[PDB]
Structure formats: structure tokens, C-alpha cells
Image 1 (cartoon, each protein chain N blue to C red):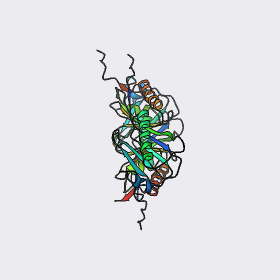
Image 2 (image 1 turned 60 degrees about the vertical axis):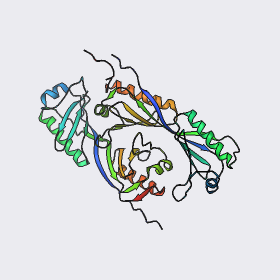
Image 3 (image 1 turned 90 degrees about the horizontal axis):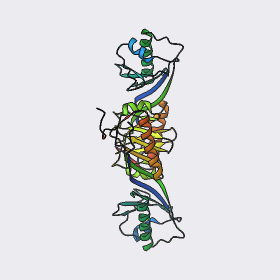
Image 4 (image 1 turned 120 degrees about the vertical axis):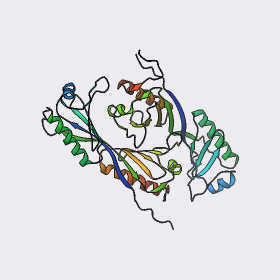
Length: 193
Length: 189
């Protein structure tokens, strides 16, 4: 019988960059914007936190802003607009539309099958499976360019992708390779009698 | 005036995975019957499993003559293991052409940086990394030169995988350590 694809992908976090194309005086911004933090002796950027959704924005003197916490593109965009609106309400001006670039997407997946890591470790290429050091199998994938953490339970962590379709491509790819190498057991399905 | 933070990391090789090319196709069914205490069940795994004790070494032998040897924690260890394995393969009938070449496929190492690492700060100052504690407690760094993956914990403990030479392992550790110091992300214990 053929093992059906039942993997479920969940985006855990997106890290993106927003260029405000202008130099910024963070001391001035900290004083102007309420409840933000700026201590250059501890961290070079001004820390702007948004609540529900939980989002953190790190603002650098170069005008580069790093936004972390969003779990979807829509969420990311709303957060950026929310952040920009505030910075505006308290003083900064924008010459043009800031561009948003995704730097990394961290996602999790559930393959819904048990993975034989001991077996996969010697039939897959480019990986680490040293259970006494890390409980999962680490696979450095080239296309797409991501790193995978794969656990015997079928749970996985995918990092390195900049687009959601790359995340999904990597999951289906390792799943298909694991099935091909006969390294998975679909325990959620009934068994041969 | 800040004290200098000298390099004090200690690296330890945890495992080496290597391949040994016996130059010949092999009948694993025959090898399993001839060599005592080995395992071959092609319905479960394509290679014959040959395990050594003291030190614990596992050798996977495929029909192509390719042999994967795992378990050794040093180059010397690796060599002694390969000689022992080939030795008994011969003691039981395998005719060995010439000198089999040995190729390191991966080295897994650990290191103690001996400094406390601020993962939250390094996460946003370094590139190529993941730090999502809910998914994995350490920071994962994909390095290009050498081509290795680093797992870094706030305690200073590290895991290094992907290298094929011991000097690459040391280079990687020194490199990330120097980067962390430059970004002011480490503190003395």
C-alpha cells in the first residue's frame, strides 16, 4: 500500500527587514516614542514592541528595521503598517514606500508518520544523526536552501526559507525521499493482518 | 575598560563517519553466512551490519563494496577499526584487491566555548541563523566557510557538524567565537 502525503506545515515565525531609507537618531526616537527601549551600551538598535499580535521591531540608525514575530505575510504587513503609523505619529517622515524583504521563515511540520532516524541517517546524504548530542536528524538541503530538524515522531522544524512555497517544497521533498528509502512507518493508519 | 575575552574553547570529536571502498561487488548473503555474528536482512536494510565492541564501531557493508564505518572518535581510531574489520572479512574469505581508500564523510564535534552566549542578541546580529526557543533551545548557524552547521547554546556548549577535516572543525569554532566577541554577545563565566 502507498503511504499518503498527510504532512501539515505551520509557520512559527517570520523575520523580515524594512528599509526606511534614511539615517535615524535613536536617542531622539526613544524620547519621542513612548515605551520603547534604546541602550546602545547593550544593543545597537531601538526596540519597539507591539502587543497582540506579539511583534518585535528592532530599529537601527541606518533606518533598517528588523521585524520579528509575525506568522503570516498578512500579519507581517499589518504589523509593519502599524509600526510605521506610530513612528509617523511621533515624528519621522517617509519619502517613499518602504520595501519589506523576508530574511527567514521558521516553520514546523508534522509528517504524521514515524521516522526511522538510524536508518535514514545512513541512506540519506548530508546529515547528522548523533542522538547523544541532538535527538533529531539534521539535514542541510540545497534546493531549497534550508536546514531541517527531523524527529522520530515525524515532527520537523524547517529554517532558511524566504518564501512559503519553499517551506512546503522542502517538506514534501524529504517526505518523498524518506518514503523512497523506506524509512517511515504510517502508524496512524491500520495495519496489515 | 573591558577585559579581553581570550579564546578558550575546547573541541571534542564525538563521531566520524567514513566510507571505505573495497574494490569489488559483494554477495552479502554469502558474507553473512561466512562471517559470524553479522546481520543481513535486505527486507530491512540494504547493507550487511558488522558491529565491533571496544571500541564500539559499526560497519555497514553494501553490495557495491562500499563500506560505511561509524563510531570512531579519532583518525587513529578510524584506521584501527578499518584494519580490524577488513582483517576478519579476510579471516572469513573476502579476497581484497588493493589498498582500500578511506574517505571521511562527516565529523560530528562538540565544543565548550567557556563563555556565556546571549542567544537573543546574537540572533539579530548574526546572519544565517535560527533562534526560536520554542522549536529548539539553541541557536542554529549555517556556516559557509567551512560548510558546517552549528548548534550553539547559551551555556557555551556547541555542536559542530558537516566538516570532513578536523582543522575545519577548529576553524569553525574559532570563527563563530571571534564573531560573537566582535558583536559583544559573550560574557566570561
